[PDB]
Amino acid sequence: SESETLNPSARIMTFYPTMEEFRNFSRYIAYIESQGAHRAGLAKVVPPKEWKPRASYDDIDDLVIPAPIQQLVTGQSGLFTQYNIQKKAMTVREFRKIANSDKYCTPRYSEFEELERKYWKNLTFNPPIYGADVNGTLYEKHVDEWNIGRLRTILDLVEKESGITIEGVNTPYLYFGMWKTSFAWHTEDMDLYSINYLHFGEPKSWYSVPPEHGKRLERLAKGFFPGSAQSCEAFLRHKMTLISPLMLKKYGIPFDKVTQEAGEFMITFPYGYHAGFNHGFNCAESTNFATRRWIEYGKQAVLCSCRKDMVKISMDVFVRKFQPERYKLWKAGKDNTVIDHTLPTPEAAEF
Ligand SMILES: Nc1ccc(O)c(-c2cc(C(=O)O)ccn2)c1
Ligand SMILES: [Cl-]
Ligand SMILES: [Cl-]
Ligand SMILES: [Mn+2]
Ligand SMILES: [Mn+2]
Ligand SMILES: [Zn+2]
């Protein structure tokens, strides 16, 4: 009730940290959770105006996009399935050229609602190319604040313990977008946190569903896609499923929306379903991370059961280290802990 009194509407919150607050990443995450930001599943953090992760983005024209994907979308009435078609490798220069070309460039519009309507109206036409899942970073090696390449959260325990790297999850990914490129409805692998930084370019728009309401979205999605639901216990993790905000409203699924500008951070929280699209040519960097609060989510995450090489992180080291008194019960399959999506991560006891 202390936590349930904070952000009771579960709306997307925006934060403007000072440079002092901005330096300690995990601490500021704990803070915004103390303010109830996590209840939305998504939050925006606008960094100090003097902070910059890179002096200049003029040298990256020759950066290679090894596996650009053409996004074919099929559907109607607010329900869509996205099929990825991998294209030949190409450079950022070659990508931007195509992105800004007359055929793929952003349509003209007044307010955001107009561009949003055009997105949902034309989603299945003129399939765009997304320069997605590029291994790398655009942070300068010296930037110590909010460095996606080295956030130093307890997610580091995975590699530290096993040597295992999972691309885009405990390593950084770059996303080069063009108009009408999409990311489908999903939570993160193992229901982790994620961080997303829009380095440059046109905006990225987001939809989010509160974790305390995530199950309702799942039930809706299973109803809409019964074939997919029968074939996999977590088919949304395929990240192929697009659902319009009008469809969510029609079925009483609560949600919020936010538009991300260049130079801005987006944080997604455990079991926070989100989706969205890019307004035009841009570039974003992202990875996943953890807090102590995530551990229970990780233990209870419902994973994909049909796809091989799907991301499954062993929770053992986390339970042993941060829940020693529950380790035996958990191994015996008798840990029946129930998650309260309103509670902030325990690191926020300072606040
Ligand atoms: N395929 C995938 C996996 C995990 C993710 O977290 C995302 C994702 C991508 C974007 C993006 O395309 O910028 C935004 C939010 N989530 C995509
Ligand atoms: Cl699912
Ligand atoms: Cl990612
Ligand atoms: Mn995501
Ligand atoms: Mn189906
Ligand atoms: Zn599956």
Image (spheres, rainbow, N blue to C red):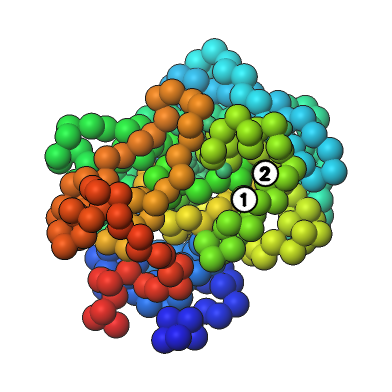
Residue at numbered disc 1? 218
Looking at the picture, does residue 276 appear above or below residue 294?
A: above
Q: Residue at x 43, y 56 (%)?
A: 270
Query: Which element type, helix, strand or loop, lies under badge 1?
Result: helix
Where does residue 132 sit, x and y in percent of width and height?
A: 51, 31
Determine if residue 226 is in view: yes
Where does residue 167 sit, x and y in percent of width and height?
A: 35, 32
Q: Residue at x 24, y 49 (%)?
A: 332
Other residues around mark 2 within 10 Å, as few (<14) / some (14–19) / many (≥20)? some
Q: Label 2, label 1: how many angstroms apart (C-alpha)?
A: 6 Å
The C terminus lies in which quarter of the figure? Answer: bottom left
Q: Residue at x 26, y 79 (%)?
A: 349
State yes or no: Cβ of the residue under disc 1 lies below 8 Å from any atom of ligand 2.
Answer: yes
Q: How many marks?
A: 2
Looking at the picture, does residue 343 appear above or below residue 166?
A: below
In this view, the residue in front, 101 or 332, is 332
Disc number at residue 90?
none
The image quadrant of residue 81 is top right
State yes or no: Cβ of the residue under disc 2 lies below 8 Å from any atom of ligand 2.
Answer: yes
In this view, the residue in front, 163 or 213, is 213
The answer to whether the residue labelled 2 contacts the one labelled 1, judged by CB atoms less than 8 Å apart, is: yes
Q: Residue at x 68, y 46 (%)?
A: 221
**Residue type, label 1:** Glu
In this view, the residue in front, 106 or 45, is 45
Disc number at residue 222?
2
**Residue type, label 2:** Lys
Looking at the picture, does residue 331 appear above or below residue 125?
A: below
Looking at the picture, does residue 28 appear above or below residue 232?
A: below
Query: Which element type, helix, strand or loop, lies under badge 2?
Result: helix
Where does residue 285 sit, x and y in percent of width and height?
A: 43, 43
The image quadrant of residue 99 is top right
The N terminus lies in which quarter of the figure? Answer: bottom left
